[PDB]
Image: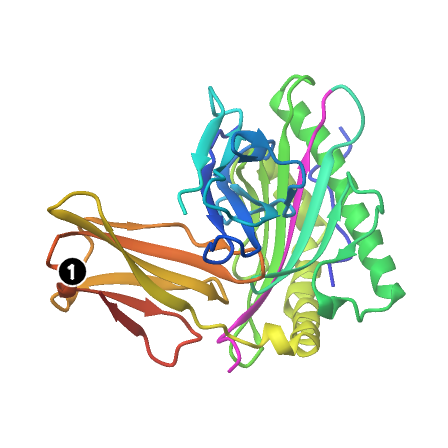
Amino acid sequence: SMPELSLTLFDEPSIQRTPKIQVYSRHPAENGKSNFLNCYVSGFHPSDIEVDLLKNGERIEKVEHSDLSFSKDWSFYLLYYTEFTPTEKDEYACRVNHVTLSQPKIVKWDRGDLGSHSMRYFFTSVSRPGRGEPRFIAVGYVDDTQFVRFDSDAASQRMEPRAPWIEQEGPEYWDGETRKVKAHSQTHRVDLGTLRGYYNQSEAGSHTVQRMYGCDVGSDWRFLRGYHQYAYDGKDYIALKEDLRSWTAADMAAQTTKHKWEAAHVAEQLRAYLEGTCVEWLRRYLENGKETLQRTDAPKTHMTHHAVSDHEATLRCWALSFYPAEITLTWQRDGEDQTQDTELVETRPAGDGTFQKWAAVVVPSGQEQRYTCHVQHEGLPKPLTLRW
């Protein structure tokens, strides 16, 4: 499934973004009903981060988290979560520390087939000055569904399943993905060392490389787009262009890499993978995971009303439990678009494979009924309108 070979950057001789934080339950919170408390952190760089869920101020010990992944702009996101049963008295919060934060930040818990398909592999390596190899985390996605992962800190040293429908694949599959992913981790190990040497950075600092591969297919599952991009310290380094036959080098180090990869016909070999292999395995996964991968889950929508004063109210339009993640929430007033005085949250994972989002508008108390929330999602044959 993964590409077979990765070539290092060269021949033989740091962005700081602060985390956004959302603290929320997976399901509407009812006292006495088991639930999951989520702390979603996103848009941060570098990837090192400290996240604790708190109950009445005390660290919760049985807290798990998602495999490190990143967005198009190379910023990282992680879901931390624990199972809990809300009560009336208990208070929960998320405590985050990161190199961009002078003090820890505490956010209180306030309480048909898809129209197109993609496969993505994301790789992150973080050097560890002073001893040993980089931390290496790889994840694979079909659409918005993670299905494999490799974590160098995990005990198995194996590519591991993260979706039920990938477990069908036989031992040969897991041996091959394990072999390829470990080879990719060594490419990054070399790359981190040579990049440090190109930029004359000290051995005492931790740096990051990020790599992504993927293919897109349209509603017919035929090849639409292929991608391959590489970043150093959260910044573009080199990217394969749309035509899959040339490169975009961001600086002179990447320009040397472009020359090494051009002479070695990297793009020719990647084109065959992105155009063929990648799509073929995507289609195989879509067929084996059909029950979920080919199912759209329309958003479950409702509205809440919050009065902060006698003259001011907040209307919140909620979209819950939807899949895939792409969704549009808009407000209208008297049937015309309204963007003034609105707030939209980043779409976030519920933790059960579905996604959540809300949109809010501040309105004059008594005028709620002028406003309508409009929900567009490919699981809906027609957009939804909600009104208080």
- State whether residue 316 is above or below residue 61: below
Is 4 included in the stretch rendered in magenta?
no
Residue 252 falls left or right of residue 176: left
Image quarter in which the C terminus is found: bottom left
Which region is colored magenta? 112-129
Indicate the position of residue 138 as horizontal and vertical percent values. Answer: 70, 48
Between 48 and 87, the one nearer to me in the picture: 87
Between 222 and 71, the one nearer to me in the picture: 71
Amino acid carrying label 1: it is: Glu
Is 117 included in the stretch rendered in magenta?
yes
Q: Residue at x 50, y 46 (%)?
A: 87
Q: Which residue is mark 1?
A: 368
Between 91 and 364, the one nearer to me in the picture: 91
Q: Residue at x 41, y 68 (%)?
A: 300
Between 136 and 162, the one nearer to me in the picture: 162
Q: Residues within 10 Å of mark 1 (few under 14, many from 20)?
A: some
- State whether residue 264 is above or below residue 296: above
Q: Secondary structure at mark 1?
A: helix
Indicate the position of residue 130 as horizontal and vertical percent values. Answer: 76, 19
- State whether residue 79 is above or below residue 232: below
Q: Residue at x 27, y 69 (%)?
A: 386
Q: Residue at x 12, y 53 (%)?
A: 365
Indicate the position of residue 97 as horizontal and vertical percent values. Answer: 53, 27
